[PDB]
Length: 170
Length: 170
Ligand SMILES: [Fe+3]
Ligand SMILES: [Fe+3]
Image (cartoon, rainbow over all chains, first blue to last red):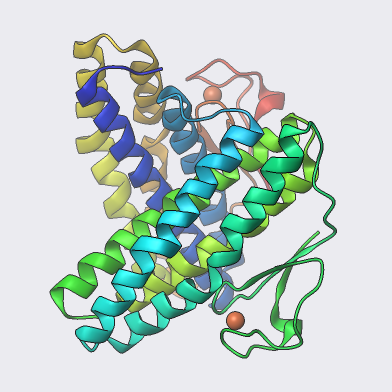
């Protein structure tokens, strides 16, 4: 575990910076695939994984990687903050400032994020009993991030997208 | 595109926050798999993708997504900052502070990162002219992120990992 303040701050910065590069490259990979450049998309995804390794290395160096129940709890805390504090305020500020796209993106998140913390809660209860959760698949709306395990609505409650649009994790 | 200064800053913060969440959940997926929780891992990977949706949404609202050659230039700039500014300073700081774990992870990136800007440049000259890149395979070292196109090295020059350790993007 890194203990010195500046170095710790620097690793935290580098974690956020590699998180954002990894993310950009993922977003850029999708765009490349769409514009008909599949080897470029593969390039972005490979380098996106390189940045995952760097962020993960920094993360583990800060001592932030624990066992699954502890990791689920960091996630519960993170999700709670996003949905109880950050998105409600950001949404309100976008509305107050008349920023319509930002009203959209924060609105989607505000309605799509709630379930996360709940799902991590359940998971942690079963993982601390030394068991896995009993889930089959998870549906994610590609438009607004709406999230459902096992069963899902015929249309996304957030954006109206049909279930056939949903990304399935199984 | 979001213009007003506060809604912009907040969207930038949301982007960084959702990038870190996505990243943490990928890292937690790995640890769940390794501890015998493939369904919790499945959940982490699913939710991680939902975070990519929100991040993407804020990224696009900020007007930061464009054409592939334009995205490749954004990558060239990011990568260059990391090579020449961020990591050299952080690594010396870690050194100066005696934090050996930080020295390693910043050294790993210092060496393994230099690759990316050049790969993105060779990719940009092709995409400029409406062509894809010819590269068939990309190998990433899972320990240090060392990056090699088409053939993995017999060992990783940076961490010394054997050839068989490299992750393949085909
Ligand atoms: Fe939706
Ligand atoms: Fe390596």
